Image (cartoon, coloured by chain):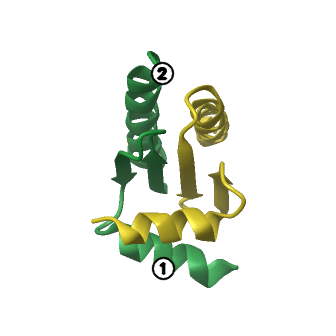
Chain colours: A green, B yellow
Amino acid sequence: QVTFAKRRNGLLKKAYELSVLCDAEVALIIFSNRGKLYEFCSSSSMLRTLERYQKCN
Amino acid sequence: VTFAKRRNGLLKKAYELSVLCDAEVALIIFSNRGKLYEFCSSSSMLRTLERYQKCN
């Protein structure tokens, strides 16, 4: 997927921007079709954000 | 607020990435008031988070 790198980088960047601009807590997990993991979390740790998520629902 | 705009944009682009590049995507967003928004491309958010935990 020739556009994968571009879209991935764009999404990681915009996730970061949302967290910075709006004081929002953001977690983003991406697996490529080859199974490569890319991720962003705005908080002290991804685990903490996932734990926060589970507590709602 | 431009929170709404950027949020909607991110949710949409996450969807596009999953569809256009056959990628598995999970996205969790808490507003500064603690409102939860989310997108997951798979059958369930839990399954994708479980996949995530299995890596390093």
Q: Amino acid at mark 2?
A: Gln
Subunit of label 2: A
Answer whether residue A54 is visible to the viewer in this image: yes
Above or below, A40 against A14 in this view is below
Residue A23 horizontal side relative to residue B55, left or right: right
- Image coordinates for residue A11, horizontal then vertical, percent: 46, 34
View extreme (front): residue: A34
Please tell me which residue lies in front, B28 or A3: A3
Q: Which mark is residue A51?
A: 1
Q: Quadrant of residue A17?
A: top left
Give the mark nearest the N terminus, 1 or 2. 2
Element under label 1? helix
10 Å crowding of disc 2: few (<14), some (14-19), many (20+) = few
* Residue at 47 percent of width and 42 percent of height: A18
Position of residue B1 relative to residue A23, above or below, is above
Q: Amino acid at mark 1?
A: Glu
Give the labeled residue for mark 2: A1
Task: Return the chain for callout 1.
Answer: A
- Quadrant where the image shows the N terminus of chain B: top right
Q: Nearer the viewer, residue A50 or B1?
A: A50
Residue at the image point whose x is 65% and y is 37% from the top: B15
Quarter of the image where one finds residue B11: top right
Residue under the image location 45 percent in, 40 percent down = A32
Residue B7 in the image: state x and y as whole percent. Answer: 61, 41
- Residue B24, position as x, y percentages in the image: 55, 47
